[PDB]
Image: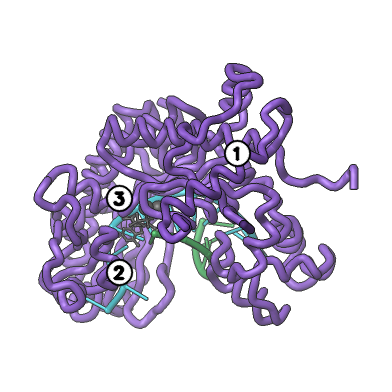
Chain colours: A purple, B cyan, C green
DNA sequence: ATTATGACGCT
DNA sequence: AGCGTCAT
């Protein structure tokens, strides 16, 4: 009753750039715009690996982690842009710089947490407060929300047959039910959050050309879930009240962090399918199956409640370079291993020097990760050393020193290496 | 031969 | 410190 928290204390958004690498290439090459298009890295093996897909191409069944030669089977007129290759490896600088463009625009509106190169959470609570003070009493026009969907609406009682008519009918029902006079209203606060996110997305598109989708809700998990409900180039508001119906048919694997082994164990141990079915277990039961942390998180989350804060962090925490050496390309000699460590270290030094100049910080730890042929784990081995100088030869030599005992016997390297990974971590101000 | 990255938890 | 998990 009057003491049960409802998780309605914040307004949180998740902004996702639509098929981001594709949009970057389409801005650069207008011939790719409004066409079935994909971004591919490498070329020789099966036409290269597709890593990003325009929505026009997705309509043909093209997906990420598909060989370009196969995608061309589904979509013969598919257009391709290739990731830049530098020092024998993919070089993602263009997309990192485009991401900075977008994140810097977002940070004018509110505090952002950079979740991925194409994804940021937005803590809007303060901004909504301020905007509500700017409009105390003024109702919110549907015109301020021209790309917003209200999840769960319309509901109940002929233009209902087109998606935009559905969208506007749901929005109308929502706005007609609002109570503009109450400044503490969670639904009103979400609505103003959505107004601000429309403004943010307009500014991103005006100033970069890039479109995005967004979710607006009371916490990061719901905002992330909401963002995916209406894509591309749209945004979705998930209210607290929408959660019981939304979760009642929502596969557990769709909630962030439950798409892997933990979600699978939840399904198998509890014998359920949908997020809402979790409400019928006590907090102690969930803790007994999944641990104290996971159980408390599940108990609250299936009720729409989550407390993970939007961390104020615009910049990545790590700067890493890695390359897989699959199949017959696996590294089998000492010279090979050392040459590729050098290539990785040279890209790393370039990026680290640029980072130190841009962001007034220096990395202090170098993490060296490798995978050995036959091992299915992402990393077979991780070892750290001190990162004391932004010097590619020193960094590559140090990484070799740290990994070289993994070699059984040689000039020869066995077992062959299928992955090398250098990561600069543990930044401090400079 | 479903990349090249990121973020983060457990012990 | 080193390994495991989750994500596109
Ligand atoms: N596994 C991977 N390999 C390469 N690039 C990747 C990647 N995962 C993400 N990216 C980068 C490169 C891609 O630009 C993007 C793909 O990740 P989403 O954000 O999950 N999906 P998208 O942006 O394509 O569209 P939308 O979310 O609107 O549906 O992020
Ligand atoms: Mg995206
Ligand atoms: Mg994304």
**Which corner quadrant holds the C terminus of chain A?**
top left
Q: Which mark is residue A20?
A: 3
Q: Is mark 3 within 8 Å of ligand 1?
A: yes
Q: Nearer the viewer, residue A48 or A142?
A: A142
Which residue: 56% across, 26% down? A127
Task: State which quadrant residue A161 falls in.
Answer: bottom left
Which residue: 34% across, 36% down? A102
Which residue: 37% across, 30% down? A104
Tell me where residue A95 appears, x and y as whole percent.
26, 46
SS for dot 1: helix
Q: Which mark is residue A175?
A: 1
Distance from the alpha carbon under mark 3 to that under mark 2: 14 Å
Distance from the alpha carbon under mark 1 to that under mark 2: 37 Å
Tell me where residue A395 appears, x and y as whole percent.
28, 48
Q: Is mark 1 within 8 Å of ligand 1?
A: no
Quick one: label 3 or label 2, which is nearer the N terminus?
Answer: 3
Q: Nearer the viewer, residue A219 or A288?
A: A219
Distance from the alpha carbon under mark 3 to that under mark 1: 32 Å
Instruction: Name the residue carrying label 2.
Output: A63
Q: For this view, does A266 lie left or right of residue A326?
A: right
SS for dot 3: helix
Mark 2 is surrounded, within 10 Å at the Cα level, by few (under 14), some (14 to 19) or many (20 or more) other residues, namely some
């Amino acid at each position: 009753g009057p003491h049960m928290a409802t998780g309605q204390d914040r307004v949180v958004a998740l902004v996702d750039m639509d098929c981001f690498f594709v949009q970057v290439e389409q801005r650069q090459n207008p011939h790719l715009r409004n066409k079935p298009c994909a971004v591919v890295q490498y070329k020789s093996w099966k036409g290269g690996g597709i890593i990003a897909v325009s929505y026009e191409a997705r309509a043909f069944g093209v997906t990420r982690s598909m060989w370009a030669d196969d995608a061309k089977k589904l979509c013969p007129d598919l257009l391709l842009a290739q990731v830049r290759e530098s020092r024998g490896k993919a070089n993602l600088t263009k997309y990192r710089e485009a991401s900075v463009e977008v994140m810097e625009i977002m940070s004018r509106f509110a505090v952002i947490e950079r979740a991925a190169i194409d994804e940021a959470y937005v803590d809007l609570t303060s901004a909504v407060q301020e905007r509500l003070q700017k409009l105390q009493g003024q109702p919110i026009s549907a015109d301020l929300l021209p790309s917003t969907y209200i999840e769960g609406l319309p509901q109940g009682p002929e233009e209902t047959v087109q998606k935009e008519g559905m969208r506007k009918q749901g929005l109308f029902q929502w706005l007609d039910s609002l109570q503009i006079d109450n400044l503490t209203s969670p639904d009103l606060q979400l609505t103003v959050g959505a107004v601000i996110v429309e403004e943010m997305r307009a500014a991103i598109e005006r100033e970069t050309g890039f479109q995005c989708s967004a979710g607006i809700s009371h916490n990061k998990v719901l905002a992330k879930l909401a963002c995916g409900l209406n894509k591309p180039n749209r945004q979705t508001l998930v209210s607290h009240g929408s959660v019981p119906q939304l979760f009642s048919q929502m596969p557990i694997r769709k909630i962030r962090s439950l798409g892997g082994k933990l979600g699978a164990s939840v399904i198998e141990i509890l014998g359920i399918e949908y997020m809402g079915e979790l409400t019928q277990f006590t907090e102690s039961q969930l803790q007994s199956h999944f641990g104290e942390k996971n159980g408390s998180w599940l108990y609250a989350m299936c009720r729409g409640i989550e407390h993970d804060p939007v961390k104020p962090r615009q910049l990545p925490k790590t700067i890493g370079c890695s390359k897989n050496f699959p199949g017959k390309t696996a590294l089998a000699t000492r010279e090979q291993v050392q040459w590729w460590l050098l290539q990785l270290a040279q890209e790393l030094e370039e990026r680290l020097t640029k980072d130190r100049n841009d962001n007034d910080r220096v990395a202090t730890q170098l993490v060296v990760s490798i995978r050995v042929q036959g091992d299915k784990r992402l990393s077979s081995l991780r070892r750290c050393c001190a990162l004391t100088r932004y010097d590619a030869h020193k960094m590559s030599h140090d990484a070799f020193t740290v990994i070289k005992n993994c070699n059984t016997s040689g000039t020869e390297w066995s077992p062959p290496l299928t992955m090398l990974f250098l990561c600069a971590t543990k930044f401090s101000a400079s």
